[PDB]
Length: 294
Image (cartoon, rainbow, N blue to C red; front, side, top):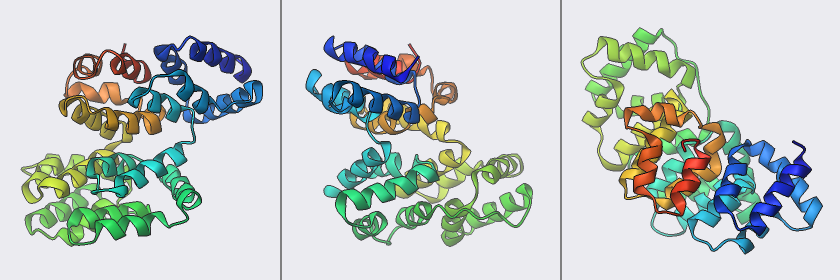
């Protein structure tokens, strides 16, 4: 279908105030494609698509999410990061915005942040986070998105990694998780598991607790695959009594890139069923539509 025709579908769904229908249309198209659609929409009707959505819907995280899907995902992410820093540091939001992110999207987000707030994002972040804990240090290095191929084979690398865990050489840990390329991480994690008593995940649990723990744990999933981190962060939202704010962050920014989440979710259960239980009558059908698990 032509973008003008999709824009018309959206017009009528908005007029109908049909939330699931807006979610369904959004779910059909990637972030880039939804940008094209939003362009056709404003040309056709002379109003911005997120502005029309906001005016048509009641509100709550449902409307915000739907708006986000037809907004600039880098401005969206940048504002989430601002929000996470505006009060007490929002560590959950940190995971959603900093760790569940491709380097490309991060780069554009940093540019959006300068445009929106006339401040350097990373500087603002480290200002409020500090460097007194290992999670802070990993996040700083993560944001650099400077991945560096590792010297040895997967088995040699897993052994050095294991030795680092066993000796609590946290400096090696921060540098490893902060700079290892994802493509290399997967074979390393497999070799680790195969040769050592613990898997990498169990090793993390042995040395870290609280925010350190969750930061390295998210990093682990991220390196395995963004859809696998997505699966985990959706399960967390379900378990945290239907965390609407997290679901809005990760769905609004990342749903198109993480649609494999439903398959990776099988280790926790049935994603569709879990969303059904944990989220209310309005939000749940929206999420299940977007994540393609009706």
